[PDB]
Length: 239
Figure 1 (cartoon, rainbow, N blue to C red):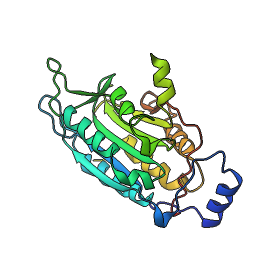
Figure 2: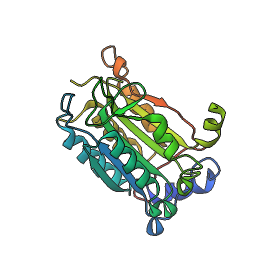
Figure 3: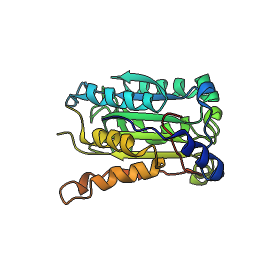
Figure 4: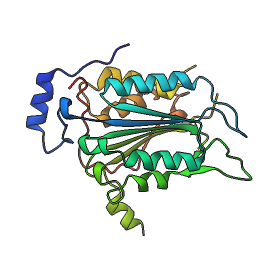
């Protein structure tokens, strides 16, 4: 229904008592949080993803309620998806932000998400590794030490340097095969609305996952992947 807000006194108490345990929050009047939604709905060689407008609308409204300015991209090839991500990573607003969200919705394979022109004979794929590399501690200094939340809906889904430089990420992934709004996005929005005022990000994700704890829904439970957060991320909605 509505995003429940965190009382300002609870925000202050938690930020004072648990300051070393949670990501710091920039004050609301000097803050310029950005979020990005990429959604592919029409493909040259894949079924359409109808009702995506409802998922986009819901996620945009949720993120704006969480005080993110939302850029929406639709129906891009893998090349253009990577371009959009690099452009977003260089935005100067991130300097005066405390965090970001990246929401990706398309068909997917194991290694990444499909662009609009993807075919099995001529693949068009944005690799997940590319996403994490674009925003890592070397390549995105303005988001360094800040939580980078990647929400992925992709139907039909040395490393020591990677472990050192890819920090403060979390990915929340649904790979439910295709067939209004999608179940994963609806549950995600409901749990943020009901719980983000009191629980940190991973507790919200766990409430989402618990909603799939039934015999017939368990196979579709979204997964937390590539977790490298060093603190807990409280959103303090309304603050």
